[PDB]
Length: 236
Ligand SMILES: Cn1cncc1-c1cnn([C@H](CC2CC2)c2ccc(-c3c(-n4cnnn4)ccc(Cl)c3F)c[n+]2[O-])c1
Image (tube, rainbow, N blue to C red):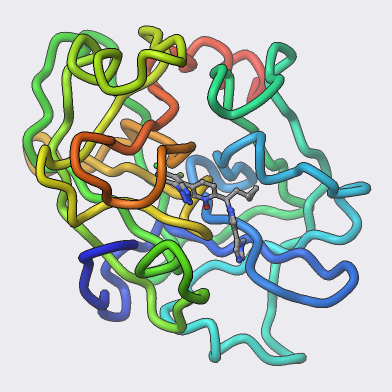
């Protein structure tokens, strides 16, 4: 996260850190708890992942340094990537992880609601992006989970900034015209979380952008409301 600040314990309890363990253990991507056995993340995260065997899902983590050899994690039973996914910038950047067992929800690990039916024309004004990613283009994975408030951009404006890509209704863009706050390397797969009527909704999945927090280049997120039918089909 560029231009963000440290979170505190319990602040974003649907945020998980997805680790790979091949050839060594490290944070790979963010993700969001959406059901007791379900994580929503980005399809692009699984480039070069040979199988679910090498993945570990950690919930309730504030600092990456908390994770030791006896820290409990969830195994991944299945990775479900959208059948039309080809590359992040072309869309369909969405994946479900089915966990090997059910999360018992606690103060530190909680689900986030999907965008609610009948809310498609809501204007979200309280949106946040979170993650352990770089604070600048050439940086390093951060120890403490970071947060930044970022405004949504219309798809018309976003397309004008990305005339070499097809910005579709299944994408949502977020960023300041002057730059300065954005997702960056290591944040992808995590949530764009928006609060509406004091309820948090998973509005976006952190996906791609031109650089990090550059002027007039918003971050691009998978527009989760356009995938609710797909999510419900797979989780049922
Ligand atoms: C894990 N890891 C450890 N060391 C470095 C990484 C690392 C490098 N790439 N990634 C991922 C893609 C990789 C998982 C398959 C990525 C790509 C792009 C953006 C991004 C960008 N960025 C543009 N240029 N950089 N970021 C801008 C806006 C937005 Cl919304 C974004 F989602 C964010 N992530 O995470 C992680």
